[PDB]
Amino acid sequence: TTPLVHVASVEKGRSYEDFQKVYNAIALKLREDDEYDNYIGYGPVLVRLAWHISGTWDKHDNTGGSYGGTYRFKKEFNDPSNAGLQNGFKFLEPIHKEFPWISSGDLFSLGGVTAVQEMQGPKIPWRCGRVDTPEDTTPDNGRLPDADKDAGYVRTFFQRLNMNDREVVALMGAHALGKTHLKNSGYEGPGGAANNVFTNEFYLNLLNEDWKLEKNDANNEQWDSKSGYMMLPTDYSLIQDPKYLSIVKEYANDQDKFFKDFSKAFEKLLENGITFPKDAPSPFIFKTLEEQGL
Amino acid sequence: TTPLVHVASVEKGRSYEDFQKVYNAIALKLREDDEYDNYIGYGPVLVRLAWHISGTWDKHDNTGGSYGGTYRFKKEFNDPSNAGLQNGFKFLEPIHKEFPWISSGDLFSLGGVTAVQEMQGPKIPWRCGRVDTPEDTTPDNGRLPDADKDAGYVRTFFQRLNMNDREVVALMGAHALGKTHLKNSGYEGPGGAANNVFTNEFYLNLLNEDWKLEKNDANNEQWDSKSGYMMLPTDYSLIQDPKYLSIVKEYANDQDKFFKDFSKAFEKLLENGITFPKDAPSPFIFKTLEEQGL
Amino acid sequence: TEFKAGSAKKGATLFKTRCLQCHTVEKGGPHKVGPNLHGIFGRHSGQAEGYSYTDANIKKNVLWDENNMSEYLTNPKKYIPGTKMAFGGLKKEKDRNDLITYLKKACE
Amino acid sequence: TEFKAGSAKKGATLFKTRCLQCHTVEKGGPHKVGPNLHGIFGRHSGQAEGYSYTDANIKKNVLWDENNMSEYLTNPKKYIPGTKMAFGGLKKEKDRNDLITYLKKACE
Ligand code: HEC
Ligand code: HEC
Ligand code: HEC
Ligand code: HEC
Ligand SMILES: Cc1ccc(N)c(C)c1
Ligand SMILES: Cc1ccc(N)c(C)c1
């Protein structure tokens, strides 16, 4: 029967100038709603949403992945256990109503892309063609990484997402955006000062901040800094593992190297499980709101 | 020595894309501070500002107009025809600092064009090349019309602006936007329900409402309707005069015609006194925010 | 629910400036440029008596709830093409939440 | 001046939920990722007493008053490129009207 084949089918009569409009609507709503989560913005929750829906992918049976966009169905997410993402969705469906022609998968993939570029991040090529598939396909959770694990778990997990050491250290750079909410995951606190700005501060803190193993009120252990910063054990595992420790120090010295790598990785993650027919156009590169005078 | 010759020279290395940047900045700030004047916005005052600037033109000796764009002090804003315009200048100078390359006249005219289009008006072609001038070029008071006159006054006044009968009934339709202010002009109230949405309500309200002469708190007379509306004596003269009345009814039955003729009239008004070279670019038709996805 | 709850005290001030001129609220309200807004939540579009609606307003026959309202109020001509309601549209979700919060109680 | 001021209360949150992670408000405050922000009005483009500072900002050496520095928080990379000031920002005039008022008073 072979693993599933998800083929990118572009929305009808839709080109670059259409998805740029959607991009803009996302980016402006980011700027209109700045009071979310003690003035952090919907930036972080949108980058996580894209990661989470692209993270259920399984290269062995080609199940899950961003293509499906089946995540609007309730069976998908338990809510909680993956808590915090219900805000990411409540941010997008008015934009889904402004543009009812775009597929769900395309939407919160673009939102994940729009969020980064607006948060001073690198420019990430994005593609259209992901199609909603709730019928017969609703990826069960438990496919997503636990927080309390280590470098062995991370490495063996991301190979399922077809990611090598370099890619997963790059994608972990996103954990400089936002914070952990104790009410959602069981961990509390940010791991950086700039929570709404895409930088390399992540790799800097790991190597330059001192960390103590501390319990939180949710009884789970974590690494906490003197500055008030924190890290997940999965994040802290990256300085524990020598192969991971090498790549970490590189992005700490060169931020531009990280921007090029995150772009390559984060795009790959979004396009995982999708076979693009050769008649499909080159990946879009969207202009930000700043370079449009806005 | 012949009347003053004003040649339109574009700023150094400027094009279409550069000006939409300013347009977008204006259109956005127009949306941001929407609390101004009891949620009417800076829409009307930007339109009026453009009118008042262009309204200083004299076709006899070619003085005034929007070319020079050089007046910082219309004899101070308190008593004469210009009261309330200082709020429009305060809207523009933060936009003028991020674009110090743009001229005053262009920023004054474009700001007028931007407001009309953003208030769902017609598309108004705009041109660049206005150059700033020194002190001895400053237009003065007494150039603009008084509110309480008759149709004979309006006719002979707009002659100086090179505007015929049809071209003034079109422009007076702009008085569907905003309201008169007693603290400013000496007249109080709106002449319509939609003050921040460009329509032909001015012409419908004019001959479908019941108007009666009444004295406001500034002891000036005006035409009020029982729906709470008001019309300047100059506005009401447009149905007193038969030649004006025929056009008023026309725009009342056809808004699409009114939009078409307003654009030609408004563009002409903002372009009076300008000599455009032949190697100069074609007029600009800018994209609105709603067209860019906003 | 997807929409949030705002303030009727800053939702009424938003009504007195942007809506009150075209719309009344309380029982037996006089028909202005727009109809009387009372019992609008739970009734179909353009079903208030004694008012002349455009076709397009009645045609969609949507049932006004607290969410599809905010969709119509951000772009009145986009949600119902051909409507004769002239309004710029609310672009701040707060303004939409605060107003509907007021409209929910004002229009009980 | 041409730039108004806001209430002395609301944006105290906008210093603690927004600018607290970097800037301190007290006399001789301990330096963080940002310098001790006190006496800022009347002082220079990055005095930064006892704190690491790139050349990219004292470039201007312009005093920080209410007027000249209103473009400072709208887009940092725009008014002083190549800097290390990285923050989300605010695009509405109210918030800028606000935060200055507390660092016009508590930064005396
Ligand atoms: C906030 C500023 C506003 C709210 C909230 C509503 N309006 Fe209006 N309104 C106006 C007209 C001419 C109509 C009828 C249009 C047509 O039938 O095609 C309406 C209608 C509504 C409705 C729909 C009611 C129904 O379908 O039964 C709602 C929910 C509504 N209005 C709420 C006029 C105007 C207007 C004139 C200048 C303004 C500023 C507003 N409306 C603004 C609001
Ligand atoms: C870090 C996460 C910051 C946030 C959030 C804000 N600021 Fe900032 N500030 C930060 C740094 C790293 C620096 C200077 C260091 C360098 O090398 O450039 C500053 C500096 C300022 C200054 C000028 C200081 C001086 O001596 O002239 C000002 C006036 C200032 N910061 C204000 C400010 C405001 C108003 C903020 C939020 C609304 C804000 N900062 C956020 C780091 C960070
Ligand atoms: C490419 C992006 C990306 C990847 C890959 C990623 N995350 Fe995250 N994650 C985010 C973002 C962005 C946030 C911040 C969300 C917020 O602040 O609400 C986040 C937050 C979290 C949170 C806290 C959420 C909350 O509401 O408290 C947990 C737990 C978490 N991540 C676990 C993981 C683990 C474990 C891995 C891998 C082993 C991982 N994530 C990989 C983007 C990512
Ligand atoms: C093309 C545009 C245009 C033309 C032409 C025009 N006006 Fe107006 N005028 C406006 C707008 C828009 C306003 C509303 C300003 C506001 O609401 O702040 C206004 C307002 C006014 C006001 C009141 C301002 C206040 O603050 O109360 C007066 C007085 C006035 N106009 C006089 C005139 C007279 C007299 C004429 C012609 C005989 C004229 N204008 C022609 C656009 C125009
Ligand atoms: C800055 C940051 C972002 C995300 C997460 N999960 C953490 C711990 C820190
Ligand atoms: C609707 C309106 C707007 C402005 C002015 N000036 C008048 C008389 C009516």
Image (spheres, coloured by chain):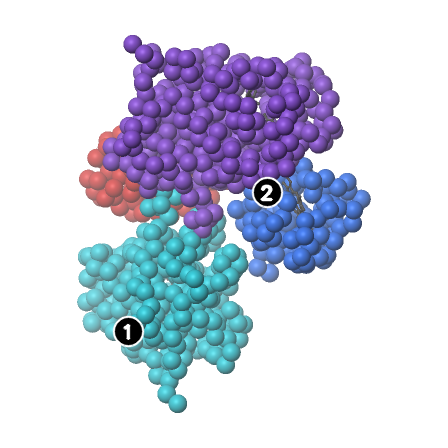
Chain colours: A cyan, B purple, C blue, D red
Q: Position of residue A146 (x, y in %)?
A: 39, 74
Q: Amino acid at mark 2?
A: Phe
Q: Estimate the spatial distance between the alpha carbons at disc 1 and disc 2, rounded to whole Å.
A: 51 Å
Q: Amino acid at mark 1?
A: Met
Vertical position of residue A172 compared to residue A274: above or below? above
Q: Position of residue D107 (x, y in %)?
A: 38, 33
Estimate how packed mark 2 is, as few (under 14), some (14 to 19) or many (20 or more) residues with alpha carbons within 10 Å: many
x 64%, y 20%: residue: B241
Ligand 6 is located in which of the four quadrants? top right
* Closer to the eye: label 1 or 2: 2
Is residue D59 visible in the rendered image? The answer is yes
The residue lying toward the viewer, choosing from B147 and A80, is B147
Vertical position of residue B293 compared to residue D96: above or below? below
Quarter that holds the N terminus of chain B: top left
Element type at mark 1: loop
Q: Name the chain under label 1.
A: A
In the visual, does B256 lie left or right of A224?
right
x 67%, y 57%: residue: C59
Vertical position of residue B247 compared to residue A126: above or below? above
Asked if disc 1 and disc 2 are in contact, CB closer than 8 Å, the reply is no
The residue furthest bottom is A1
The residue furthest right is C28
In the visual, does B258 lie left or right of A115?
right
Estimate how packed mark 1 is, as few (under 14), some (14 to 19) or many (20 or more) residues with alpha carbons within 10 Å: some
In the visual, does A235 lie left or right of B120?
left
Q: Position of residue B292 (x, y in %)?
A: 43, 49
The answer to whether the beta carbon of the residue marked 2 is less than 8 Å from any atom of ligand 1 is yes
For disc 2, the marked residue is C87
In the visual, does A161 lie left or right of B50?
left
For disc 1, the marked residue is A163
Q: Name the chain under label 2.
A: C
x 24%, y 60%: residue: A260
